[PDB]
Image (cartoon, rainbow over all chains, first blue to last red; front, side, top):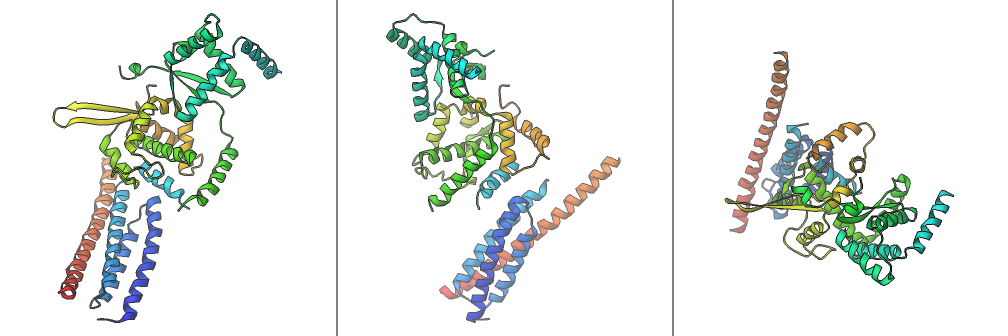
Length: 101
Length: 261
Length: 48
C-alpha cells in the first residue's frame, strides 16, 4: 500500500461516486433528514483511507477531507432534524431546491 | 349591458372629469418606475393643481377618489386603497379620510394561466445565464424569503439574525454590489422601508447600544392575503388539500400579532 | 401515571437512540482525528 497507482485512482473514483451519492443524500436530508447516510459515508471514506494508509498522494488527502467536511455537516443536520418531528428554513431551501431542476 | 351602460355613465363623468385620466396616468407612471405608495396630501395637492388648470371649482375629494376607483375597476378591475397612518400602528373605507394610497389587483387566480406564465419564464431562465423584470423579481424574491423568515420569527427578528439567515442562503454579506442588482442589501432594506414593506425597530439598550429588529411593513401587510399566503405555502412545497387547515393554523401561529388585525 | 409512563417510554427512546447517535458522532470524531493524526504525519514526512 505505498504507491500503487491503481489503488489511488480507484480511491479517487469511489470517492467521486461517493460525492455524487452524498449529493443525493443532501437532497434526501433536506426533504427528510437521515443520519444513516452520514454515518455510512463516514465509514466508507474511513475504510478507503485505511486502504490509502501507506499511500501518500496529497490529492487523496484533500478530497478525503472534503468528504470529512461534507459528512460532518450531514450528521449535524440529521441530528437537528432528529431532535424533533425551521420548517420554513427547510421549506425555503426546498423552495429553492425544488426550483433547482 | 351593465358594463356598457356603466362605462357610458363613466364616460359622462369623464366629460365632467378628464382629470381622473391624467391622475391615473401619473399614478401608474409613478408606480411603474417606482412601485410607490402616495400620500393623501399629494393627492389633494395634484387635485388642486388640476382644479386650477381645469378652472373649475373643486368637487368632493371623496367623490373624486370613488369615481376614479370605479373607473379603473370597469377598466382595470382594481381597487384604490388608502392606508391607515403609521402612528396608528405603534401607538368603512376611509378613502378621502385615508392617508397613503396605492392600487390593488382584485381578480382571483386563473391557475392554468399563472402556471403557463411559470412555463414561459422557465424557458427564460433556463436560457438566461450561467433583467429589470427579473431584477425586481429577485429583489422581491429575497423579500419574500425574508417575509417567511419574519413569519417563523413571529413578526419579530433582529438585524443580525436576519443577516445570518441571509448568509444561510448564500447571500454575500460582504458589502459587495448585489449580483445582477449591483447594490447593497442595505439599500434593498431602505427601499422596503420607503416601499413600506418592512418595519425597522431601533432601541437604545444601555448595555448593547441600539439593537435593531424588524417586522412586516404595511405595504406587504395589506398586500399579504391570508389565503394567498396559505396557498402560496402549499405551492412552495407542492401540497395537496390534506394539510390545508393544519398548516393554516400553523401559519396562524407564525403570524400571531404580525398584523394589526 | 400512564401519561407519565408514555412520556417515560418516549423519552427513553429519545435519550437512548439519540445518545447512540451521539456516540456515532463521537466515533466519527475519533476517526477524523485519526485522519489528522495520520495524514498530517504523512505531511510531516513528505514536506520535511
